Structures are given as structure tokens and as C-alpha cells.
Image (cartoon, helix red, strand yellow):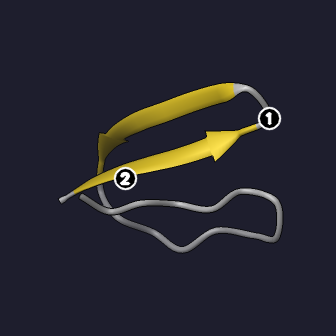
Amino acid sequence: SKYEYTIXSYTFRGPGCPTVKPXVTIRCE
């Protein structure tokens, strides 16, 4: 499991799958 949580124009991709606030939308691969 790896979270890709995208903020603005920057894709932040690493380990641990949490849930996110309105605006940011995570992907657990």
C-alpha cells in the first residue's frame, strides 16, 4: 500500500494510506 496524495500542482507519492480533506484526493495503490 502506497499513498499518492496530490496538493495543487505537486504529486506527493510514498508509504501509508490515510484519508484526506476537500481539495486533496488520495490514491492508495
Given the image, on which type of amino acid does mark 2 rest?
Answer: Tyr
* Residue bearing mark 1: 8
* Residue bearing mark 2: 3
Discs 1, 2 touching: Cβ within 8 Å: no
Q: Position of residue 4 (x, y in %)?
A: 43, 46
Residue pictured at 55% horizontal, 31% vertical = 11
- Residue 14 to residue 29: above or below: above
Q: Label 1: few (<14), some or many (≥20) within 10 Å?
A: few
The front one of 1 and 27 is 27
In the displayed structure image, the side of residue 9 where residue 26 appears, left or right: left
In the displayed structure image, the side of residue 22 where residue 13 appears, left or right: left
Q: Label 2: few (<14), some or many (≥20) within 10 Å?
A: some
Q: Position of residue 13 (x, y in %)?
A: 39, 36
- Residue 21 to residue 26: above or below: below
The N terminus appears in which quarter of the rendering? bottom left
**Helix, strand or loop at mark 2:** strand
